[PDB]
Amino acid sequence: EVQLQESGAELVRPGTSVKLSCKVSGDTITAYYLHFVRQRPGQGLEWIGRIDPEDDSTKYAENFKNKATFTADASSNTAYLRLSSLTSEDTATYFCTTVTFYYSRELRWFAYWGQGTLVTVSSAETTAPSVYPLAPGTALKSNSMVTLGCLVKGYFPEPVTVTWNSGALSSGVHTFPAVLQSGLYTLTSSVTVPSSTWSSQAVTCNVAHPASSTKVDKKIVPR
Amino acid sequence: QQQHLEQLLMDLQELLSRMENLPRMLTFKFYLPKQATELKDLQCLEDELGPLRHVLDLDAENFISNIRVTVVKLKGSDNTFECQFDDESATVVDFLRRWIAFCQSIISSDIQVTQSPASLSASLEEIVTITCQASQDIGNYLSWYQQKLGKSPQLLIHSATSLADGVPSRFSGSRSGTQYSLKINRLQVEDTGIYYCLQHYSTPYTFGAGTKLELKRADAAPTVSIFPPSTEQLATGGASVVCLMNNFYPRDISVKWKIDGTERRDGVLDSVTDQDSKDSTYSMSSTLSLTKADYESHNLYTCEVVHKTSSSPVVKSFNRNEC
């Protein structure tokens, strides 16, 4: 029943602070200790610290003493983590997760996790991405397969969400990890579909970049 | 021996006596074994000292800590009895009364954790073991978690040995003193992913460094596709040629871009997907970024791919001059 929602600025400038939030639904927040965990890219989970909404009693990891402050409001059912003196090493995904002794044993230890929220510390500015279709250089064969794609070039910061046909195509899809080069990210997404579906139905990629409030849909057309 | 028991009894009598004298600490849910008849059953008491600590409000740490050392002295240290808890919960009071009764009945530094291996590839139906080693006696206060595609971790095994609700029955947890083992009884396709242990015995909590598990598969040749710059992009003054290699195994592969017969290495970006959770293959994207000016100065663009599935390199090309 319970869900936790992490939210916060996607881009922050070195030396500033950032304030993350954890919105709990499906139950009161007074039943949970709320713990924050971060994961730098291609690294493992690091426990940041926790706060007890009951009394605001907090605990911190060694390495986040004097970086981190936990705060809460019960009536808003949301927990806060403030992180100060930011450097590039703070660029990471932040999750929140729970401990509880008010239910079963199986529900005590980090049973629930937020979806996670990426935070980039950087001096660069929010750059909207450019979307370009990858369409077959050679024409259609009736009864076969076909692979289409979208280049999403030159955006900052992470992340971007790609879909195909607003969710209707989920199989046959590969969205590759973005690559930074010269301050900008570039990713491709592909989808493999029947030769019939391409001529009969429209095939479109929907790319979102919430950091720049960009929304782009692009139909892939033969060339 | 029986000086240890009576000391425990009085410590538990002390706890019960000074617990009763608001209805806020009565919400915490403790759990008891079905049967508690031997000294080695005191493992089940040790397992509940975590919550027992939290309820103890208003440096009582010393009290629980010294109870624990007494229990460790009493339960046996030779072997690791797994406790079997009843589903029915108890207040802090009834729990205390129960263990007190059991005692009367029977009288007649930050914690480091090392995970290993760091990475592993294994076949379908294989039995896999992952280990965590704790720097200290942490008892049953370690749990195992899974994570895929950098998404939300998911609890697999809690309290060293208990399966979480929701988790496949093939996952199981074992403990021998300070050695903890996550075992996957006959690996499935969807098991590709990262596994982490977490000590949650005392603050600060600590995760293991993680284990990257990949599935072995039979070989699979890539589907190779090359794409010229879109007219839309050329208009913008850029020219990205893209090569997609899809659903290949193993992951080890090499791609060269040639322009009119000559290798270009600058302006190339490579990206590889994580192992597919349904087919255990990999896919790869190679993009060669040129200026429109540069792109329009040459004719033949080739993506040349080396993979073990072919004795000669797989080649995909286009001539700009046609399109």
Image: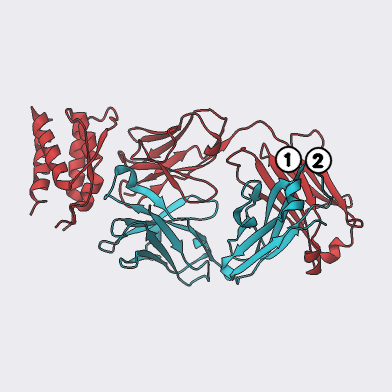
Chain colours: A cyan, B red
Exactly how many numbered labels are in the figure? Answer: 2
Label 1 packing within 10 angstroms: few (<14), some (14-19), many (20+): many
Q: Chain of mark 1?
A: B
Identify the amino acid type marked 1: Pro
> Which residue is depicted at the point 63% across and 61% down?
A207
Mark earlier in primary sequence (1, 2) = 1
Q: Position of residue A181 (x, y in %)?
A: 67, 61
Residue B59 in the image: x percent, y percent?
19, 55
The structure residue drawn at horizontal position 25% and vertical position 46%, both measured from the top left corner, is: B50
- Numbered disc 2: secondary structure: strand
Q: Residue furthest front?
A: A200
Whole-percent x and y of residue B8? Answer: 13, 39
**Residue for point 65% across, 42% down:** B282
Q: Quadrant of the C terminus of chain B?
A: bottom right
- Numbered circle sitting on residue B50: none
Circles 1 and 2 in contact, beta carbons < 8 Å = yes
Where disc 1 sits, the SS reads: loop
Horizontal arrangement in the rendering, residue A121 relative to residue A193 (left or right): left
How packed mark 2 is, by other alpha carbons closer than 10 Å (few <14, some 14-19, many 20 or more), is some
Toward which corner of the image does residue A178 lie, by quadrant? bottom right
Give the image location of residue B254, x and y in percent: 74, 43
Q: Nearer the viewer, mark 1 or mark 2?
A: 1
Which amino acid lies under the numbered mark 2 shown in the image of this protein? Val
Residue A59 in sight here: no
The answer to whether residue B194 of the structure is visible from this angle is yes
Identify the residue position indicated by label 1 in the image. Answer: B222
Residue identifier under label 2: B314
Circles 1 and 2 on the same chain: yes
